[PDB]
Image: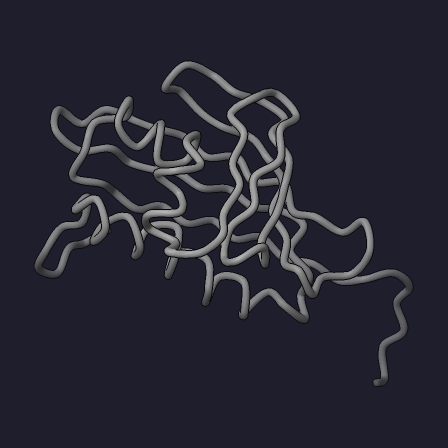
Length: 145
């Protein structure tokens, strides 16, 4: 290329979707291996614990729990099985109460630009798209999100 820059480029994946379930509920689907292997239908290994390891997509997506707040928010790493060495993304999820639904505010920063698109493309497809249908925490009709 024309521009010269050292290191690897990255991007941010800010996804804000709502769920037709209470925080405490979704608070498990993300902190419960089993629940994960349900919406992922693939060999997933989740360990609810500060520093634990969460694997999904048949061992294609792994990470590590950095912070865990009571039905409040969750901060962990996110990456693919084809990502560079020691290269993860800091993802900080948040569960909000809307009196029936839960607004999951995902904030990922550090996703490889080269895999940026791919990431987001195959991020919710399993994260939400999977649960929304699996557990039935999805809505219908067009919204002004």
